[PDB]
Length: 142
Length: 142
Image (cartoon, rainbow over all chains, first blue to last red):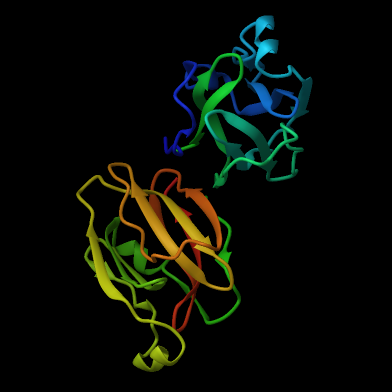
């Protein structure tokens, strides 16, 4: 399927949710949010991906941890855009669906910004992670 | 049908390539390019749409004209994304295919930018036009 540019930096380890996405449409967005977004974990059907970010508690040296946020999506609800601010890491993430505008994860939005539109809805994400979210790529449904 | 939202302003006249797209998958992109994109004209199989933009040569009384640009797509190459800057009009357009990012049409990229993913490849465009490209909507094959 069509995918966006990779947004972020070259650090961290690669992740790619193509396989876990076989379980279903995205039904839920879980993130950890402080002045920046420190992890993302989508639910595909009833199956979560792994926690992409906040590799371990020693990461508190390099950023705050943040609050666990959970946005449940209804059946037929899908993510139609993502506004990402990023430098060497993803700084903040704002998702919009065909029903809702979700709050920004990451109170700071000072880095360069990109708006990715995903007609028909996001299928899954890939990117890089470690203590935080090094980068993201958005994969469309076809 | 999956399609993007309409990007641009309310001027000019609507156009819609839905009917002409029955002639085939997109095989070529023709645009006219200066500081802004002043027309677009796709080829569907062997058949072109009308020229959407630069309605007449007296348009030089409001904007620059630009030079003709043609991108020929290979068989099995399809348009997967467009980076569009826009306000009252479409300002610049950067197409990407499943094989390559193409050159931007319109050297000025200062207005609101979005990266439109076009799932399964672009099937056809609709929009509005006059002396320039008042707006665009991308209709995906999938």
